[PDB]
RNA sequence: AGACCUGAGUGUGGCAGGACUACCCGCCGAACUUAAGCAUAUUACUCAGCGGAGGAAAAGAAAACAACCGUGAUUCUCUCAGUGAGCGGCGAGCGAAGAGGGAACGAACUCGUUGCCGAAUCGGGUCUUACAAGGCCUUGAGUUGUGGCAC
RNA sequence: CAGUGUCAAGUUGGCAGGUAUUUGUCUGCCAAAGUUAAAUACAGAGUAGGAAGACCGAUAGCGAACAAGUAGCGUGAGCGA
RNA sequence: GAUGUGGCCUGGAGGUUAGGACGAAGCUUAUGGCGUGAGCCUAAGAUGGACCGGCCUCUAGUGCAGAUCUUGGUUGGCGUA
RNA sequence: CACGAGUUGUUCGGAAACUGAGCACAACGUUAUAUCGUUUUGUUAGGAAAGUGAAGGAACUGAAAAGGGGCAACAGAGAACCUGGGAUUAUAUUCCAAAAAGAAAUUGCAUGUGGG
RNA sequence: AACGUGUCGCGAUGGAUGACUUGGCUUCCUAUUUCGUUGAAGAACGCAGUAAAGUGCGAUAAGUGGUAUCAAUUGCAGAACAUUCAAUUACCGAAUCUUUGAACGCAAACGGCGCAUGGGAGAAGCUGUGUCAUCCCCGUGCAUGCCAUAUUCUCAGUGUCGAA
């Protein structure tokens, strides 16, 4: 990410931005997406999108509406 | 005692001379501070210390500005000691600059020129 | 006899002062700190003791550099003209 | 150089030698052994203390004995050469 | 005993220097709340163990 | 002689380790507990453990839904729905999705391939008031293919 | 989804269409490179500012209204007024 | 054990009415009066020093004699062992 | 308890500077995870880990030499000083001043005398 | 009568209650809002005329510079540009910033020991002056890995070729 050729290339210089540091550690590459189940969409992937934890969070948290 | 204005108008050799005199004076006052001494004599230790601080402040500000203007030339910029470069932040120093951020492919530029964003209204 | 007499039998010390954290948790024989894991590069940190983490985290010292850079960020790295 | 600060060689001896001592033992050493007693920089050398004595008081240190006090300061017992009088030097120092 | 590393000696020196009572003029001050050092240490009461 | 191509040494320019860790992402991963016992189940894809980033992250431009008079990237909210879905010693328990009203929304782009070109590319020196998206030079890298154009 | 074995097809084609199979129709879409703002989180974080409360009122409210993660304790992890 | 009570009581809120340096809250009582009672109210302080009562409605961390109850203080044993 | 003092080294002890039982940086391997393992039976690592005696025309070049860098003993190894003092309130083989009370030993550099 | 009981007035011990709250807890919002090899967080040691803790700071040390503000700080002392040079305050661009710590020349219950390179001081001899061996002091660089690179550096291989 420090090479000038990389930094001045609009096709690859997205990876210079620090949100992509160690993206493989976070399962963000193609192989990580594969084992996360993110090759599938719709009814074959509803319980794992945008992640398993995200779906668990929105399926298991108790909602208290103000007027209920 | 030393007004900062006089020190700005003072040369480097003269600054070093007056630093030596103020250091010597503070040393003598330390001797007095050991053997009792009068309140008036003990009470000039702090002005002498603050004057020494002023002389060192002028000396270091002048040295750093002169060095910065020395390494600012095209030839010697890339060898600038890291203590003279802008600090900012580690991530900001590593981050893409606006020119690098704004790079576009030639097709992207042609597309941006072919269909600019317009201003319009409806009645 | 265990108890008072054996209290008399205790000589030496398992721990001395740690160079890194200063806690008297440095195991002399093992040459590692029981409090901060020195000389391992990273410190000890365990979620089963949030209290110890809150004792040791950022802000329990003086934050001598953090305050300055926080001010510079807050002022948008202002420089003379 | 990555160190830019203006350091001058004409004030280092003021860091090496901090101030003299005036206790009864120090006074007895002035009178009886031609010896001055100073608080010095705790990281300073015996050799540097001799050089700083020369530079600050124009006097020759024939022997420097040092110790670190239980309060954390380094004290120097400095015997001058017989060509110099400790009492006269102490007076000029203001001791 | 005789042996100690200089660093331990300096820590003990700082503890000696801290084992002092409060100056009285501190008690004469305008918003003062301190009257005793409250961190005084006796060598027989509590150990530093350096 | 020499070459490239595989691998070393040193000089030069730079980067990683640490901290934080509420939220977020990847792994790993219990038991108490509930079932009036208990082993499947439950607690729970939770706690504890190991990694990683940000101001949010992750997701995201259909190998999507539907079965309609059709919708149209992602995320989120109400609702669908504690469900005449389903899972379950079909016990205890568990348990979503599409459609609908909405928040947001200038939301869309890149490569690879194909086919037409084929160094037009990159880095480095050095000029232009300029480590220019510029000129000149440059075997240094690159033809074991960078870069342009097109549906 | 993972390990291992085994491993395609080529739009006369694949994938999906929530009861396995073999047929033959229909519908939607085109996996196995990649980037992307907002609307969402902040369930024991931080920086700089702000606004509040039918809350607590010194054995309460944070452990801490105070030189409090202090004094003190523990070999230590920790404990903690 | 159930239920009722223009039944008693406490901290706050919306209302409405008052009181207080000519003395609020708190505290003391051979200090009387009222109520079956929970309690209310007056008097006197040779008490105190600045807030607070009544009534309707709203609200809650709302009533203690005991839990080998929690914290603080005291206490007989005892001028004893 | 308060105030004010006090610990003096070429040779003493340590370290500079040894090896031991052992430890484990690097290297490599393993592990979803290095915060794991190997690491003295002469000895790391599929492993190219030596950087300078010389010369030769003042610092530049380079033979041969197998098995990286450390740590671990204040009772092992090692280590050139020792008496006198009328010398303290408190230190002393540490202080003493030219008659050093004095007497030595031992390093590192330099200067002369002399050499066979 | 003596202990001992009761009741009342007045005292002591003891710190409840009430009023007071620069604190806590909870909710909401705004942003050119997110540290570190340019050495962080954290540890340690120091710094005031008087100074234990705490706060603030770092050998320029209860602070230097700057811009505002305008007459203090205050326990004592000390100081005495006012049209702003204040021990005033507030804010912030310039500076400083000890020993450490990822800690990175090698080590470490050692304020220890190096290599390279710049400096400083320097006795005795030399013409008070310069010069200076050993010794001593200071600056800078020097971990490992990885990437790029060498106006095209130095090499290795019974790897593949090939000279004329
Ligand atoms: K103890
Ligand atoms: K049960
Ligand atoms: K909709
Ligand atoms: K109260
Ligand atoms: Mg000594
Ligand atoms: Mg000890
Ligand atoms: Mg269980
Ligand atoms: Mg439970
Ligand atoms: Mg059971
Ligand atoms: Mg966990
Ligand atoms: Mg995102
Ligand atoms: Mg992405
Ligand atoms: Mg209290
Ligand atoms: Mg409390
Ligand atoms: Mg009953
Ligand atoms: Mg309440
Ligand atoms: Mg209650
Ligand atoms: Mg009862
Ligand atoms: Mg005492
Ligand atoms: Mg061994
Ligand atoms: Mg050793
Ligand atoms: Mg010795
Ligand atoms: Mg202090
Ligand atoms: Mg290290
Ligand atoms: Na960690
Ligand atoms: Na002893
Ligand atoms: Na890190
Ligand atoms: Na971050
Ligand atoms: Na599989
Ligand atoms: Na009670
Ligand atoms: Na003392």
Image (cartoon, coloured by chain):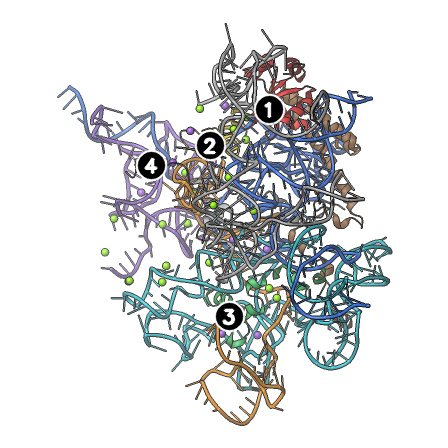
Chain colours: A green, B brown, D red, E yellow, F cyan, G orange, H purple, J blue
Quadrant of the displayed image that contains ligand 1? top left
Q: Is residue E3 visible?
A: yes
Question: Which marked residue is nearer to the observer: mark 2 or mark 4?
Answer: 4
Q: Are marks 3 and 4 on the same chain?
A: no
Q: Residue visible at 52% across and 72% down?
A: A37
The Cα–Cα distance between marks 4 and 1, rounded to whole angstroms, is 44 Å
The Cα–Cα distance between marks 3 and 2, rounded to whole angstroms, is 59 Å
Binning the other alpha carbons within 10 Å of mark 1 as few (below 14), some (14 to 19) or many (20 upward) gives many
Q: Are marks 4 and 1 in contact (CB under 8 Å)?
A: no
Q: Which residue is mark 4?
A: C7
Q: Which mark is residue E39?
A: 2
Binning the other alpha carbons within 10 Å of mark 2 as few (below 14), some (14 to 19) or many (20 upward) gives few
Label 3 chain ID: A
Q: Nearer the viewer, residue E8 or F45?
A: E8
* Residue F124 sits in quarter: bottom right
* Residue A18 sits in quarter: bottom right
Give coordinates of residue G18: x percent, y percent.
47, 82
Give coordinates of residue H42: x percent, y percent.
35, 38
Q: Which residue is mark 3?
A: A48
Q: Is residue F48 above or below residue F68?
A: above
Q: Secondary structure at mark 4?
A: helix
Give coordinates of residue F62: x percent, y percent.
60, 77
- Would residue F145 appear left or right of C1 to someone viewing this image? right
Q: Secondary structure at mark 2?
A: loop
């Amino acid at each position: 990410p420090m090479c000038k050729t990389i930094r001045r290339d609009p096709r690859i210089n997205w990876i210079v931005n620090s949100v992509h540091k160690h993206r493989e550690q976070r399962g963000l590459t193609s192989a990580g997406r594969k084992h996360r189940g993110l090759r599938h969409k719709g009814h074959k992937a509803s319980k794992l999108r945008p992640s398993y934890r995200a779906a668990w969070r929105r399926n298991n948290r108790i909602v208290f509406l103000r007027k209920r | 005692h030393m007004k900062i204005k006089d020190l700005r108008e003072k040369s480097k050799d003269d600054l070093l001379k007056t630093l030596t005199e103020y250091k010597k004076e503070l040393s003598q006052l330390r001797v007095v501070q050991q053997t009792g001494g009068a309140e008036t004599r003990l009470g000039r230790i702090r002005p002498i210390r603050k004057s020494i601080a002023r002389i060192l402040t002028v000396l270091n500000q002048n040295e750093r500005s002169n060095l910065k203007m020395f390494y600012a030339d095209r030839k010697l910029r890339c060898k600038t000691p890291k203590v003279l470069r802008t600090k900012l932040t580690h991530r900001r120093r590593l981050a893409l600059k606006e020119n690098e951020k704004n790079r576009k492919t030639s097709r992207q530029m042609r597309q941006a020129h072919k269909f600019p964003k317009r201003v319009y209204a409806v009645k | 006899t265990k108890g008072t007499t054996s209290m008399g039998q205790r000589h030496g010390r398992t721990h001395i002062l740690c160079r890194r954290c200063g806690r008297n948790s440095y195991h002399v024989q093992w040459e590692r700190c029981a409090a901060c894991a020195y000389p391992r590069a990273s410190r000890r940190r365990y979620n089963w003791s949030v209290k110890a983490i809150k004792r040791r985290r950022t802000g329990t010292g003086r934050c001598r550099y953090l305050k300055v850079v926080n001010r510079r960020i807050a002022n948008h790295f202002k420089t003379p003209k | 150089s990555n160190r830019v600060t203006v350091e001058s060689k004409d004030i280092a001896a003021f860091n090496v030698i901090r101030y003299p001592l005036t206790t009864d033992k120090a006074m007895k050493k002035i009178e009886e052994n031609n010896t001055l007693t100073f608080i010095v920089d705790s990281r300073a050398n015996k050799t540097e203390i001799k050089k700083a004595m020369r530079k600050l008081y124009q006097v020759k240190a024939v022997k420097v004995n040092t110790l670190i006090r239980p309060d954390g300061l380094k004290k120097a017992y400095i015997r001058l050469s017989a060509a110099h009088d400790a009492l006269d030097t102490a007076n000029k120092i203001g001791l | 005993g005789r042996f100690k590393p200089l660093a331990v000696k300096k820590k003990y020196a700082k503890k000696m220097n801290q084992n002092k009572p409060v100056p009285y003029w501190i008690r004469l001050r305008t918003g003062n709340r301190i009257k005793w050092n409250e961190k005084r240490r006796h060598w027989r009461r509590t150990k530093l163990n350096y």
